[PDB]
Image (cartoon, rainbow over all chains, first blue to last red; front, side, top):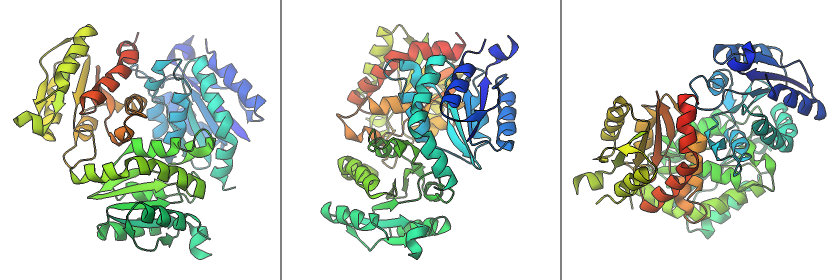
Amino acid sequence: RSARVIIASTRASSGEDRCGPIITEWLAQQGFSSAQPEVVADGSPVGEALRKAIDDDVDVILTSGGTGIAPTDSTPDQTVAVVDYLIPGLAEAIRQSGLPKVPTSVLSRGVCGVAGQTLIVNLPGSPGGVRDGLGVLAGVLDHALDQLAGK
Amino acid sequence: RSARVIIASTRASSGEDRCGPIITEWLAQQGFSSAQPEVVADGSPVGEALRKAIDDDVDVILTSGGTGIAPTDSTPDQTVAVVDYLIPGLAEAIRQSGLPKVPTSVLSRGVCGVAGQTLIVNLPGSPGGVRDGLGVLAGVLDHALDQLAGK
Amino acid sequence: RSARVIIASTRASSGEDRCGPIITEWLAQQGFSSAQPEVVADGSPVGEALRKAIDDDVDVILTSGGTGIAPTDSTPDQTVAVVDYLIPGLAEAIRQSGLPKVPTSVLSRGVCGVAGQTLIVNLPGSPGGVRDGLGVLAGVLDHALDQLAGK
C-alpha cells in the first residue's frame, strides 16, 4: 500500500505547489503510506523522479503538472519512456471527469501506465483537475492495484 | 460475411469458457459464418491464433480475454503486432459501454484494428463485458465492414 | 491568428468539396485569416500539403477527409508523421461530438497534434462531421492556441 507523489513544475520547483498537499491528503485518507512529494522541474527531472520512485518499488506513483500542450509540458513523454505499457481508458476517464465544466480538459496529454508492479497516473496541474482525477482513481485504484498483483 | 473467435485464457485453455458460446451465438444471430472458437493460452499463442485467422481471410476476428492489467494480459500487445492500423474510437466505445455500471471498464487495454481486409476487435474477458462490447459492435460492425471494403 | 485548410479527397481533387467552404466560413466567423483550402489526393499529397502549411508557420491547420477505415484513408498517418506530439483527448472529443446520432463516428481515426507552434486537427470528411468537430473546436481552440504559445 505504498505511493509516491511527483509535482512537475519548473515554476514551483524554483519558487507555490498547491497540488502536492491535496494528493498527500487523499493518499492518507485512502490508506496509502507515502513520502513527502518530490517537486521537480519539467523535462528530464520528471523522468529521473519517476525512475527513483519505481526503484523504490511503490505500488502507485501520482504525478501532477506538465500534461498540457505548453512548450515545457513533457510529463507524459517522460512517463511513456519509463512504463512497460499504457492504460488509455484510465487517462481518458481522468480527462472526461473535467467535462463538461472545463472544456479544456480535453487538452491534457497525461497518460497512465504500469512499470513492473507500479501503477503510474498523470494528473493535471491544477488543484481542481487533481480533485477531478482523484475522484476517478477513487472508483478503481484499489481494483487496479489488485488486478496488477493478480488477485 | 466470415468471422473467427479467439478466447485468450491460459486458465480456460488448460481446464470453463463462457464467452465463446456468447460470441458464437451473437455472430449466428448477426448472420456471420464462423468456425468453433480457438481457446488459447495468453501471450504468443494469441498472436499465432490471430495470424492463422488473418490467413483465413475472414472479415472479422473477435477476441475475448487478456485485456486487463494483470501480468499475463497480452492480447492487446499481440493484436497491435499483427494489425496494419488501429481504430481507437471503437476500442473507447467498447470501454465506455461498461460505464458507469462497472467503473473498472476503464482498465481494459483492448484495441481494435485492421489487418489487410480483416477487422479485429478485442473484447473484455467477462461475459457481461462481452455483451456490452457486442452491443457496441451491433451499431457499427456492418458499416465498418462496408467502409473497410470501400462501399 | 492564421489558419490553413486541407481537404483530403482523391474523389474531390480530380472532379465537389462541400467541407472546404464550411471550414473557411467558420474560420472567418472565428476571426482567423486563411488562404483558399488546398484540395489534395489521399496519401503522400496530404503529407506534402501539411508540410507546406507548417512551413508557412500558421497557428492552426484543419484537415477534412480521409480519416475513416476505407483503403485510401491515410490522413491520420500522414499527420502523425509530421507532428511533434499528439493530443488524443481532443481527437476523442471530436469523435464523441458525433455521438450518439452517428454511431459510426467511433470509426474516425483522425488525430490532433502539434508541429512546432502549429496545432493540427483532423476533422471527418462529411459536412455534418465537420460541423460537429468545429463545434468542439469552438469551445477550446482559443485556449489551446494560447496554451501552445505559453499564455
